[PDB]
């Protein structure tokens, strides 16, 4: 339902890690 704050850390972490 609310993946605004969830997808945030996910995408970011993935954009930072690799």
Image (tube, helix red, strand yellow):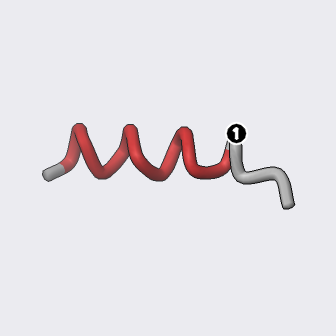
How many residues crowd mark 1 within 10 Å: few (<14), some (14–19), many (20+)?
few
Taking the view exactly as shown, the residue that stands out farthest to the bottom is 1
Residue in the foreground of this view, choosing between 17 and 6: 6
Task: Please give left or right for residue 10 compared with residue 18 in the image.
Answer: right
Q: Residue farthest to the left?
A: 18
Work out which residue is located at the far right of the displayed protein and give it.
1
- Residue 14 vs 16, above or below: the answer is below
Residue 10 pos. (x, y %): 48, 51
Name the residue beneath numbered marker 1.
Answer: 5
16 with respect to 8 (left or right)? left
The image quadrant where one finds the N terminus is: bottom right
Secondary structure beneath label 1? loop
Residue at horizontal 30%, vertical 51%?
A: 14
Residue at left offset 55%, top offset 40%: 8
Question: Residue at 41% of width from left, 47% of height from top?
Answer: 11
Coordinates of residue 5 in the picture (x, y in percent): 70, 39
- Tell how many labels: 1
- Tell me where residue 12 appears, x and y as whole percent: 38, 38
């Amino acid at each position: 339902r609310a993946l605004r704050r969830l997808a945030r850390k996910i995408a970011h972490a993935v954009k930072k890690y690799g």
